[PDB]
Length: 101
Image (cartoon, rainbow, N blue to C red; front, side):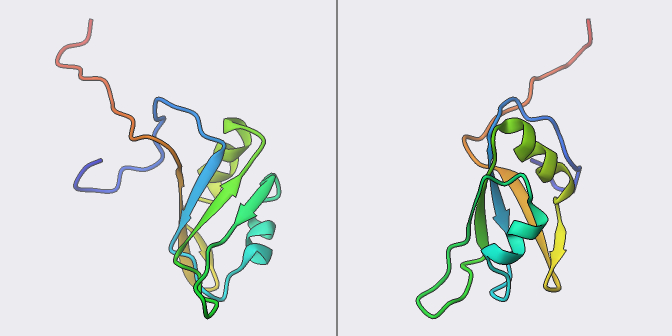
């Protein structure tokens, strides 16, 4: 959390469910099933018409696999649209550090 892109950081927590965002309507569970092979289950919420709300819910065996794909898949260009992945769950927090000991 800051005013600038940092990258993949080790958050104090573990989640087997990955939160996909920036999904294209043209993209469906089918396309996702290709990007995530370890994904034990893929969910893509669409609209009454058939348009992806703009996000998705990926499921894995554990925080192990989920992170394995979330580390790479991160910012995956699908159907001409960059998709982001974030470990679903609570909002963790870093540990202050004024002076190292």
